[PDB]
Amino acid sequence: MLIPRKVKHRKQHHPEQRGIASGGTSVSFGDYGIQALEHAYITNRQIESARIAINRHIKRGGKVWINIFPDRPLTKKPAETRMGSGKGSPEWWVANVKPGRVLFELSYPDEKTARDALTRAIHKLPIKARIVTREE
Amino acid sequence: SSSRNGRDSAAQRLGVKRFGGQVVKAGEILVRQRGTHFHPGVNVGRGGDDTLFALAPGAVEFGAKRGRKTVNIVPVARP
Amino acid sequence: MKTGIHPEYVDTTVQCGCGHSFTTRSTKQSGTIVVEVCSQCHPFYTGKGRVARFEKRYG
Amino acid sequence: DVRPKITLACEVCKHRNYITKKNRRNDPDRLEIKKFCPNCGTHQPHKES
Amino acid sequence: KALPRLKQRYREEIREALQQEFNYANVMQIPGVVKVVVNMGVGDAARDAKLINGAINDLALITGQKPEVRRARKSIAQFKLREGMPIGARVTLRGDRMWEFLDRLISIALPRIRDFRGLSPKQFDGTGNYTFGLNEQSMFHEIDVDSIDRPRGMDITVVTTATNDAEGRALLRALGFPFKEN
RNA sequence: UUGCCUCCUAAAAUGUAACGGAGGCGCCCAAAGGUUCCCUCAACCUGGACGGCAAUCAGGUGUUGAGUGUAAGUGCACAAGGGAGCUUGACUGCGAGACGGACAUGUCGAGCAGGGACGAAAGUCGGGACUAGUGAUCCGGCACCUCUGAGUGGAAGGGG
RNA sequence: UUUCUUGCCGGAGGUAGAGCUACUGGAUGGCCGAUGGGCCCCACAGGGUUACUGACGUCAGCCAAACUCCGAAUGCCGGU
Ligand SMILES: [Mg+2]
Ligand SMILES: [Mg+2]
Ligand SMILES: [Mg+2]
Ligand SMILES: [Mg+2]
Ligand SMILES: [Mg+2]
Ligand SMILES: [Mg+2]
Ligand SMILES: [Mg+2]
Ligand SMILES: [Mg+2]
Ligand SMILES: [Mg+2]
Ligand SMILES: [Mg+2]
Ligand SMILES: [Mg+2]
Ligand SMILES: [Mg+2]
Ligand SMILES: [Mg+2]
Ligand SMILES: [Mg+2]
Ligand SMILES: [Mg+2]
Ligand SMILES: [Mg+2]
Ligand SMILES: [Mg+2]
Ligand SMILES: [Mg+2]
Ligand SMILES: [Mg+2]
Ligand SMILES: [Mg+2]
Ligand SMILES: [Mg+2]
Ligand SMILES: [Mg+2]
Ligand SMILES: [Mg+2]
Ligand SMILES: [Zn+2]
Ligand SMILES: [Zn+2]
């Protein structure tokens, strides 16, 4: 799982799910990519799930880039606790994903298999997404 | 469980007390600050706590000198 | 040059066994330095196998 | 304690004019400095009481 | 009305030799020697502080002027060194007594080095200043070998208005420094 | 957990809650205070006896990434950072005009006089780059003062 | 009329947004190659090679309440 090696502030306010992505809105490494159409916190467990789905479909002979790193901590209080007594301990690592953000990129020789692989990944993600190419 | 935080000091009411064009008497405090965010200019003194105050009556004028932001007093014309 | 703090610097004569003399300053209060070797009679300043060993033995 | 309060008195008229602090380990000796003495109306030597 | 021997030789012969060799466009470009700095790094003083006084006396006799004691600027645990500890002694020689020290060094001190095979000609710092080290202090006749407690070496740097190592090497060569050939 | 100081939350004046998110304080310095004068780090490259990644020396690049007693922030290279000479203003009598604000507290202050420090002079100095290092009133102790003194002179006691 | 409202003029700011080769941290993939590591010459020295490892640097794509080279709209103080 992707976790940051260290963070300066281990308990953070929730990332704000507002606005359209101003950066990382185009495919820059591969020839195909997955572009988000909705706001979500994408967790490291979802990223792992999606990446392994792409790997299994292409088997070998391709490269997968993950343009998003889950460095934002979300806390959780211990179960069955009343409100108050301080903020919970960090539990989940998420990336703040905005519509327009390209999440995954793939290079593969065959377009049909590439698109199928990315579709397999999209079904793992909490959001709605479309396949985008380097072309206009 | 319990939090190790819950502490803070009093708000010190820092900041600009007299803005551009305001007429001030001599001695009047112009800015309260911690360092020299603003530097003393013409007819402005700097207090030991870095308070800027007027050395003569006039209008407060902000300006830049060599990049340093400065507070100045310009003499007002006598009626 | 601060007055008192320094060791006294005296006119000295340097003489060598090869006869070379020259006058210089020195800290030696005697004003005379005698020396065995100098720039002028150092060999460095002036430029001064197993088969062969076998043939020395047997030729 | 470490930095006790000391009173400086005028050497001339002995009025206790000032109170201040010193580290008694850094300065075991009685502190001697010149201060304005109001009674004398002039700077005078003052010594720790 | 006076001139140190080596200085006279510089002004009368070495300047002309350098102008013919390197063909400088302006006479102000002729390289000369600025200063000689003699440094003794008594790191052991970080514990045995008596050692500083020996290094001071040796430099005073060797150079003819009082050394300046250099304090450590930076604590370092591995050397047991605390900031502000006296850990070095340095002497800056200029003018007439820099020319005399150089003349005594080239004529008397260097040939007295034990098993002296000349100095390496590659000890220039790219800008044509020369530095070399000595392991002992006995090669100076101003120090009584009867009285030395412990061998105390030192670093000697000759700094030059030469712009490069080739020009600086030529100057010291003409000055009589005994360089190896490589 | 309870007072004080710094930051974020705090929505670009100020202020702003929670058992919200992070730390610090209940000192220290006779210089680490005052003044006059001088200086510029850290890091990196190259050369050099022990000596190494790093001790002290030399040259070069380096405008600030070092350093500011001590948290953090705002500042400071023009230095408030580094060094040196003398010194006690870490003053007495005061204080135009302001900041802050339930109140009690708290905070800044040019300038006048006395008697001084440094400086050729202009000038600066009523502690410390700045903001924590603290405790109302009562009751009582000590020193000093041209106050009072229960018939009077004293004294006790009480004032300042 | 000193209040308030509207127009205009004089002001300070660090939020929204954005940006980061502008700092402090996080962080994706190339390229380059210190650094260990393996191996061949074999001495432990100087070197030649490896499906390892990757500093520093560089090219491109990014992230932050307690990051900021930047930076609004509003609000606030004053004048008219
Ligand atoms: Mg961006
Ligand atoms: Mg605050
Ligand atoms: Mg002050
Ligand atoms: Mg002392
Ligand atoms: Mg505010
Ligand atoms: Mg606001
Ligand atoms: Mg409230
Ligand atoms: Mg200073
Ligand atoms: Mg005091
Ligand atoms: Mg008042
Ligand atoms: Mg306060
Ligand atoms: Mg006066
Ligand atoms: Mg004053
Ligand atoms: Mg103060
Ligand atoms: Mg100071
Ligand atoms: Mg009571
Ligand atoms: Mg009576
Ligand atoms: Mg009576
Ligand atoms: Mg009485
Ligand atoms: Mg009383
Ligand atoms: Mg502005
Ligand atoms: Mg934002
Ligand atoms: Mg921001
Ligand atoms: Zn000889
Ligand atoms: Zn007196």
Image: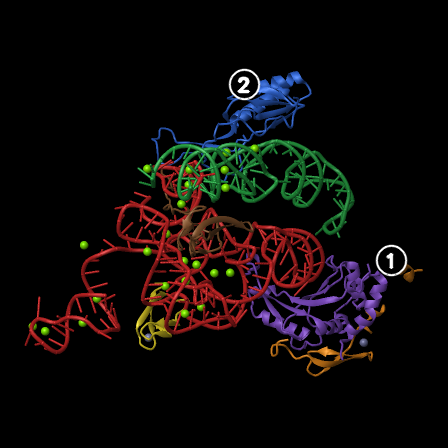
Chain colours: A blue, B brown, C orange, D yellow, E purple, F red, G green
In the rendered image of this protein, does residue C3 appear above or below residue E178? Answer: below
Q: Chain of mark 2?
A: A
Location of residue A26 (image quadrant): top right
Depth order, front residue of G24/E59: G24
Residue topped by disc 1: C50
Judge left or right: residue E97 versus residue F3: right
Judge left or right: residue E20 versus residue D26: right
Q: Secondary structure at mark 1?
A: helix
Depth order, front residue of A110/E76: A110
Q: x, y percentage for residue G55?
A: 63, 42
Residue topped by disc 2: A123
Q: Residue at x 62, y 18 (%)?
A: A115
The amino acid type found where label 2 is placed reads: His
Location of residue A31 (image quadrant): top right
Q: Are marks 2 and 1 on the same chain?
A: no
The amino acid type found where label 1 is placed reads: Arg
Examine the rendering and report whether any part of residue A27 can be seen: yes
Judge left or right: residue A118 versus residue A12: right
